[PDB]
Image 1 (spheres, rainbow over the protein chains, first blue to last red):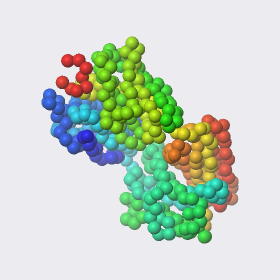
Image 2: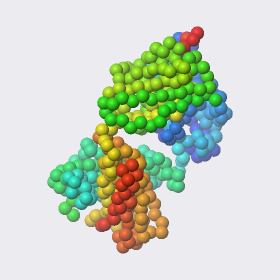
Image 3: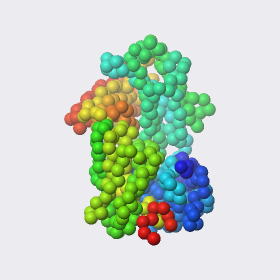
Image 4: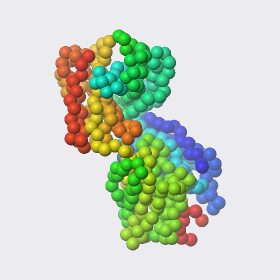
Length: 218
Length: 213
Length: 8
């Protein structure tokens, strides 16, 4: 199946600026009749995709003049000449040249603002949860920008990947920041055996991780 | 004036069957293909196949052979998607889309399907408190093991201003978990009471949890 | 000519 790769995964813009989004296919999208079946869609949260551009460069009726498409073969671009608030959302390319039709992973058009480090907070399991046999360690990473972040859990210095659950907010309307909650869920037995619990936050704003840690015995 | 209107949200258990509809208006239904597309929460769109609305012949993508059936009520300009022997991984929004000249030009609004073995289940609410500092302090509540969606976390504090975040729920092993944080001046906690009040209207359950050091 | 077309 044809792989559709979009760049970038997130595009920060100021309202009124131009935006450009790229879609690259793993094979030519020229069909045997000479047509290129490459289309562009906008999807807003909780809504269906809306067609913008079809067959590379044809604007769908009802779509504002500020959207245009270009490209050929395996390399395609959607441009917005002057971005408006109604244009924020996720942009996807599709191909139907090859069966099965496939879609790009999406490019989120978001608001640009200055970079900001996360405020990182760690919390031990509650006595309530431990009574039920369970032990969640939680790390909030709040009000950071840009969205790209990596969180690593360690127990007694050793990386733990299993039983980690992460949840990311959408871009905040007040701040234009992002926030993330990361939860490491253990058994009470496991929690009460190990001693040191650490969440490590890798973000563009720091060359070394932000590290929050506690010792159970403390 | 072209529109595709889908049936409403579904909650089903593993092993059950579901039928989703897509009613077309504003064009001749039998002139154009109808396609089905899956969108699992935070996953890429996946094409499931199409039905020829004139012949009635369905074509299934390779991951949708076996438990998926496309059918028509041509008389009602309506297409149907049936999913049998439901799996947890069928949790997704399903879309119908018209195919005209190689383009998915009009989409249905989507039908949310949630698959879980869970009956209606209230959340457990766990306080998140710092535990052996700065000008502000962040507290939270972890809301775990509930079904179905709809919880709210409402914070009360001794602070005139606060900053709250609500973290979207995730489904794991048929139950949801979410969390919420509040940030207040350190002068207001622990000296004043902070509580999170967690409502789950579907189970008519409200839990108020006071945040202690 | 497109594989999803229903009528010539």
